[PDB]
Amino acid sequence: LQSYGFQPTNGVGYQPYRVVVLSFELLHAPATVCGPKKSTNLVKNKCVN
Amino acid sequence: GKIQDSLSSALGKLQNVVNQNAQALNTLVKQLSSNFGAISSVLNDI
């Protein structure tokens, strides 16, 4: 396990980059995370999707 | 007067045809939740 050497006086491509990897999965959980969605006042008494 | 007591207190042949039909209709719907070798049972998930 070798350490990195990160000085600002080093060319790009040899500079520190912060990496965030997002991974999703969807099988059968009936109520989990959803985006900024809406639909104020649910439409009742109408065949709806 | 005794028919009325013996019944008021036997219709198995009529009950059985009702039961058989309901048991078959339930088995038909309970099959809508098998994979048969797929990733799920829902088309909105495939």
Image (cartoon, coloured by chain):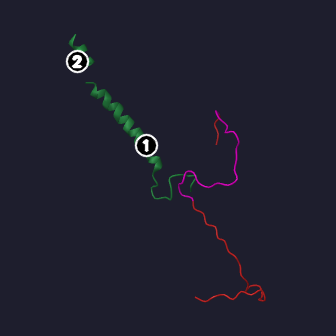
Chain colours: A red, B green
Amino acid of disc 1: Leu
Seen as rendered, the residue at the extreme front is A7
Q: Which is more toward the observer, A15 or B12?
A: A15
Name the side, left or right, on which A27 lies relative to A37: left
Q: CA distance from mark 2 to mark 1?
A: 37 Å
What's the residue at 34%, 36% (across, down)? B20
Tag 1 or tag 2, which sits nearer the N-term?
A: 2
Q: Which residue is mark 1?
A: B28
**Residue interval drawn in magenta:** A26-45
- Contact between marks 2 and 1 (CB within 8 A): the answer is no
In the drawing, does residue A3 fall left or right of residue A12? left
Determine if marks 2 and 1 fall on one subunit. yes
Q: Residue at x 31, y 32 (%)?
A: B16
Based on the picture, tell me whether residue A44 belongs to the magenta stretch.
yes
Number of residues whose C-alpha sits closer than 10 Å to that of mark 2, classed few (under 14), some (14–19) or many (20 or more): few
Amino acid type of the residue tagged 2 in the rendering: Ser
Q: Magenta residues: mostly which secondary structure?
A: loop
Where disc 2 sits, the SS reads: helix
Numbered label attached to residue B6: 2
Residue A40 position, x and y percent, is: 71, 42
Rendered-image quadrant of the C terminus of chain B? bottom right
Residue in view at x 60 percent, y 63 percent:
A24
